[PDB]
Image (cartoon, helix red, strand yellow):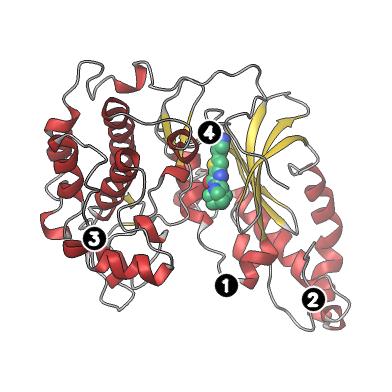
């Protein structure tokens, strides 16, 4: 029964006090309705607990605790805010996830791996989570602000030379190796998930697609997940079923990245989704480089070494194959020390709320239930404090 005490005390454990308090709060939120209270059992419970549950919710970190400096991006499940915490006066990036949209889309699991990784990864390659908290309508993740913007915005503001791509590719490679070392494969690696810190250096940021590996480093996934341009043939095929693949599905995503960075378009671009999907399946035929956009044989070799079948893909035998590829040989940095060299683009920040490397941006609650629907159950255990 001291064994029990350990589980509760561990912030990594799904039955820690904050997750047990989520448990009581979500039960009271999903029972307290006129209809359900006709049930004695439910009235007896809500009479006993409802009052103290409100008192507790009082102390819980709220949205109003933060000033919203401005919006730096909008997802399908809601927006990411540059915010300043009122009390501490510290600046964060806060991601909102609409519980209504996640419930409605039958999509209320993706965030667990994302929270786990940002909360506990403790890597200089992984954007860091300080606070997860929820209210009746929203999930909140309060992360460190990455004021350098994403690479999608860098690549569209600069002609990127090989010397830059070497750097940015190496940092992505080390970042994924970090993610892999935590027993996770990422699956949706792309420039939108690659963020630049105050010093111009890279950090992975979106993790909704990440999956625990077997004891044998494989996964059984029968869902084709991640964004179409950057998805691997093996992951696309695995929608047809009997999906069984390892982390080499991420080295594909890097090859695609490297191609886009040097060529100027994705290598399997098409007008439709199903067009891009068709091209990717046919990658032995479909991949080729424009008769102009010039690329050193080393760069072109690495790309094609990455954009092959899983069985012969660079990084199957491990990440050191990648590291000692001719393309990466350079005078600026070694792999031991890259993240303390000078980045190709060091951002010009004016203040702690400068969001100039982010483009500008510019009503749907739940209905009262008939009987128990359990709308808050999918988010028991989210709440996290550092
Ligand atoms: C932590 C941090 N510091 N500075 C910026 C950021 C982040 C910004 C961001 N943006 C998104 C958005 C939502 C959808 C639409 C486009 N992006 C992908 C999905 N997702 C994310 O995880 C993150 S982290």
Closer to viewer: mark 4 or mark 1:
4
Q: Residues within 10 Å of mark 3 (few under 14, many from 20)?
A: some
**CA gap, disc 2 to disc 1?**
27 Å
| Circle number at residue 233 | none
Query: Does 277 sit above or below residue 187?
Result: below
Q: Position of residue 124 (x, y in %)?
A: 41, 29
- Are the residues at dot 3 and dot 1 in contact (C-beta closer than 8 Å)? no
Q: Which secondary structure lies at badge 4? A: loop
* Nearest to N terminus: mark 3 or mark 4: 4
Query: Does 53 sit above or below residue 173?
Result: below
* Nearest to N terminus: mark 2 or mark 4: 2
* Residue displayed at 38% across by 21% down: 344
**CA gap, disc 2 to disc 4?**
49 Å
Query: Can residue 324 be seen?
Result: no
Closer to viewer: mark 2 or mark 1:
1
* Residue displayed at 59% across by 71% down: 105
Residue position marked by numbered label 4 in the rendering: 149
Query: Can residue 16 be seen?
Result: yes
| Circle number at residue 42 | 2
* Nearest to N terminus: mark 2 or mark 1: 2
Residue position marked by numbered label 1 in the rendering: 106
**CA gap, disc 4 to disc 1?**
31 Å
* Nearest to N terminus: mark 3 or mark 2: 2
Image quarter for residue 177?
top left
Q: Which secondary structure lies at badge 2? A: helix
Quadrant assignment for ligand 1: top right
Q: Residues within 10 Å of mark 4 (few under 14, many from 20)?
A: many
**CA gap, disc 3 to disc 1?**
26 Å
Left or right, residue 130 beside residue 257: right
Q: Position of residue 68 (x, y in %)?
A: 75, 36
| Circle number at residue 218 | 3
């Amino acid at each position: 029964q001291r064994k029990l005490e350990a589980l509760i005390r561990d912030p990594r454990s799904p039955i820690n006090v904050e997750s047990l308090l989520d448990g009581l709060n979500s039960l009271v939120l999903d029972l307290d309705f006129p209809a359900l209270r006709k049930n004695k059992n439910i009235d007896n419970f809500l009479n006993r607990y409802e009052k103290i549950v409100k008192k507790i919710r009082g102390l819980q970190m709220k949205a109003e605790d933060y000033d919203v400096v401005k919006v730096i991006g909008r997802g399908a499940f809601g927006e990411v805010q540059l915010v300043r915490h009122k009390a501490s006066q510290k600046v964060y990036a806060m991601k909102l996830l609409s519980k209504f949209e996640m419930i409605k889309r039958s999509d209320s699991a993706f965030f667990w791996e994302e929270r786990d990784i940002m909360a506990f990864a403790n890597s200089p390659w992984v954007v860091q989570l300080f606070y997860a908290f929820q209210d009746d309508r929203y999930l909140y993740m309060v992360m460190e602000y990455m004021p350098g913007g994403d690479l999608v915005n860098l690549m569209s503001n600069y002609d990127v030379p090989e010397k830059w791509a070497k750097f940015y590719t190496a940092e992505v490679v080390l970042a994924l190796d970090a993610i892999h070392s935590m027993g996770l494969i990422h699956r949706d690696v792309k420039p939108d998930n690659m963020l630049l810190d105050k010093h111009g250096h890279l950090k992975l940021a979106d993790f909704g697609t990440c999956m625990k590996m077997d004891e044998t480093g494989m996964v059984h996934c029968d869902t084709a997940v991640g964004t179409p341009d950057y998805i691997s043939p093996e992951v696309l095929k695995s929608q047809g079923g009997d999906g069984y693949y390892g982390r080499e599905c991420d080295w594909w995503s890097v090859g695609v990245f490297l191609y886009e960075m040097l060529v100027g378009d994705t290598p399997f671009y098409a007008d439709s989704l199903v067009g891009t999907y068709s091209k990717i399946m046919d990658h032995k035929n479909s991949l080729c480089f424009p008769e102009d956009a010039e690329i050193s044989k080393h760069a072109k070799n690495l790309i094609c070494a990455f954009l092959t079948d899983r069985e012969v893909r660079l990084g199957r035998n491990g990440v050191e194959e990648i590291r000692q590829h001719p393309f990466f040989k350079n005078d600026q940095w070694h792999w031991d020390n890259i993240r303390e060299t000078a980045a190709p683009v060091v951002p010009e920040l004016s203040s702690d709320i400068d969001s100039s490397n982010f483009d500008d941006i510019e009503v749907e609650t739940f209905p009262i239930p008939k009987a128990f629907v359990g709308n808050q159950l999918p988010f028991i255990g989210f709440t996290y404090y550092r």
